[PDB]
Length: 148
Length: 148
Image (tube, rainbow over all chains, first blue to last red; front, side, top):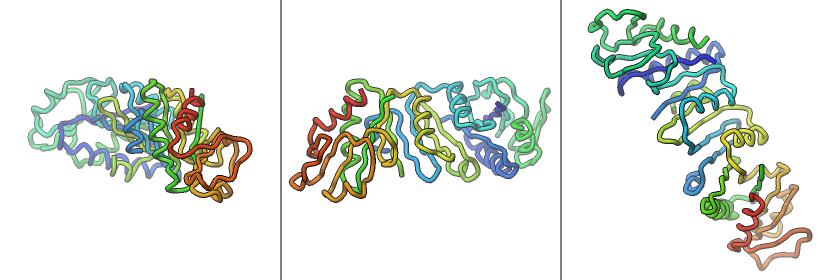
């Protein structure tokens, strides 16, 4: 069940990058979920509430969620794979967006498979993985190949 | 996995009735879901998308939903039971809200366990089940006992 993450400080270009990836996954018919780390007065009493109609479910669920259970949920709704924005702490392969060379420090994490710096001229050469410009299409293609 | 439905034309008092039921289920610690028959530009490309943070999941999922699969979903998120607004066509026990005596005709369905007429003085006596006024607490208590 392939998984790639996107991690980066606020205003790095994360949701544009993700957007580009999801658009290109539609074409290709790839069946890919998206998860972002961050009925009305029904909720003002209950825990798991939802609306459904014409093939779309809108669901709100108050649980003690961790990433593992969220991934099981995605497996249950029968997606092929998963794009995650955030959960830096998770073990899954991830693409790191840097606004500044000194972003990579506070973004402490494993299984980094690429870096999108955001202001390219700043890039001290970094061992062990490929480096792209933010608008480089290979970088969105790199993510899709890992998602299969 | 106990199930009760609430069915009735628009503006019968359905969501107030449900509200009353859910409030009283909170007290009692009953663990009960709610389902109503009827990330943003992430959706503008993908099918299953979500946001999670501080223990609440907000999920949107484009599938060919039918009631059976929605109930499995509720079983997976580990609710004890389920309150449904709508799906008149489903087999589950249901409470019917009538605004007018002639509402019961177009509301064609099985497994009706009670009627809440809404303008009580109109009630032709109806065989085979109990009859309440809209604000009768026994009627919300009747639903809770069936939910256990």
